[PDB]
Image 1 (cartoon, helix red, strand yellow):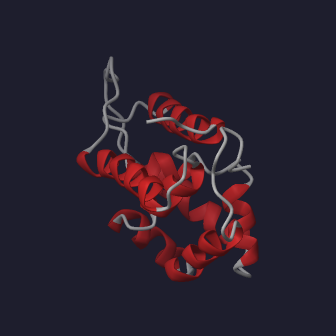
Image 2 (cartoon, helix red, strand yellow):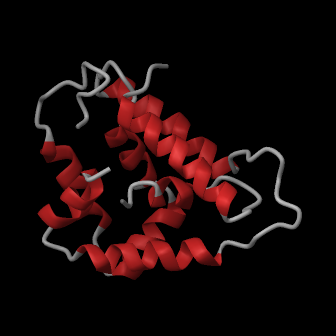
Length: 150
């Protein structure tokens, strides 16, 4: 699979967050938190007529409560659910007939994950409303370059 520049940044930043926090595994939550300053999710939340801080503070609250491990893992590996997010992002890319796995596909996959759905509900936000913003954002524009999900 080929990834957009932004998708690579999301995946790398998610791993870095897990590393810095000494968490035992890479979780869907780490991928979601990687969307926080890339201006993409902020744009969607604003389009949905929600307040960014209402979302950000909930993700951060969950992030800092992930347990830490002593000593930290030498290698951080995805949880089963985190692996499913990546597998689903690829499937969504294929269904949408896009040329690169994009930040859009990762977000759309995250919105199907139960732990992530629980976080949006807690924040006071409709997952369906956010999802509709992601669907509408680019219309029929193909993700046909490594920068096309800007």
